[PDB]
Amino acid sequence: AVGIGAVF
Amino acid sequence: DFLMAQTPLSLPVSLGDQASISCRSSQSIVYSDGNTYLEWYLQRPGQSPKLLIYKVSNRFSGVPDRFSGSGSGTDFTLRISRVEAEDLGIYYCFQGSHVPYTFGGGTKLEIKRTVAAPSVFIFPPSDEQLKSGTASVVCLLNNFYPREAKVQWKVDNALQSGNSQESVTEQDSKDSTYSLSSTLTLSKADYEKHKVYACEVTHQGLSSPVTKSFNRGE
Amino acid sequence: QVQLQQSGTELVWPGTSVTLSCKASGYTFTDYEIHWVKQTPVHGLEWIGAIVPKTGYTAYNQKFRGKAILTADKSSSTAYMDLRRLTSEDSAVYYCTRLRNYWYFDVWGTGTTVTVSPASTKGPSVFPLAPGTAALGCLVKDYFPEPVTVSWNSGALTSGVHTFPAVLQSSGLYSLSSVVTVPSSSLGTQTYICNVNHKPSNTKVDKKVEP
Image 1 (cartoon, one colour):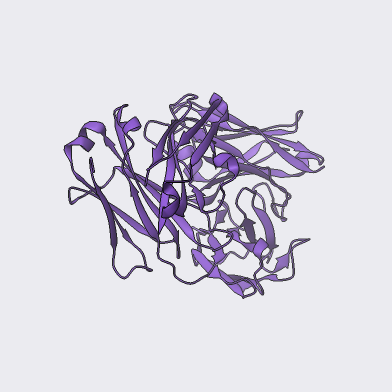
Image 2: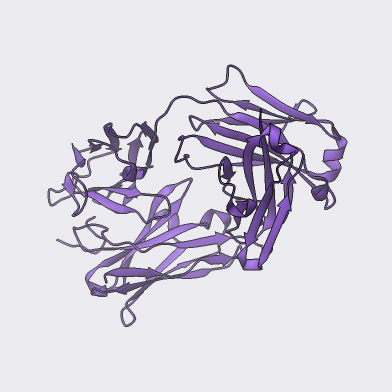
């Protein structure tokens, strides 16, 4: 998964 | 909301055959980096889920090359080129692009065999149990295929509902059949109020529904 | 060893709350998110929510908002899930699993069983299920908790035996049946005994089953 805390 | 519609619910197969499982998303699950985070997990009885495929097509390290995955957009497929005994279990697709992440409803991969009718048996409550105030009537469905079977309890020809529970064994390792046990629970006073106790069984292997019965107090 | 060590089985009364723990071992706890998954026969797998150990940031499946509270303890490398105001719908196996951003759930805990029931430890009563081919059996009734073991003729008789999954009754106590099919001819000659063991109550009972 992407993850809930990934940002960009 | 990025629900995954996974089909079919159960997939009977013969070992060595090919298996195909499909998962359809309500809208595109392509993530903003261009990747689609669509995974496939296997959960075997008594074990944790286990990762098979990630990013739609990529095999996790150690996963046999029999397993592959494909799709794009809203439509995704897991393929097993030749099914082996260790592949049996429940497969789940998983949508990891958008929160909340979601699983497909599952596909139980099982052994296909020929239709087999159940042998049906009915058991009155024991005298020992009636000493304590409850009566349990048990109906046994032995070694049938496929899994879908229906038990209907009747007391003095009146259909019962809400007073029974049942459970079904896992697929037998030798003959690939299932068995089912159903318990009708009544108070002792109710049990002594009535005479004829019957369970009627519907199954694809039976020409018509079969009823097994006893009369209380022989 | 890279592992997620989950806490043991929870036998809990309705309306109470419980803390489940997931202890990270053999990797850097704050380099991965912790995700929690609920497993049931009826709903399959469900994503409960997740926590970012580095920031304490959480996200929930709205269906579990108010039911589940996720925390992460950096100093003990442990993730926790409180499940609140338990009902029978909360009975399930709960998994934690780790996620590095953009990868996948590679390592999973072995799962924590939560069993919601008003009952306390109770040994079963064992009743006979009395009869070309005949069926006979034992009814193992009104025990808590799982499991019970059932054998026939001290384990010598395995052929034709089916021991069924227990069902949870509205009392909060389990009921289970075990049966064996045998030739109808043998019912006058051969003896059939079901051997029942419920370890939580130290109940061991053999019941002879006759026509």
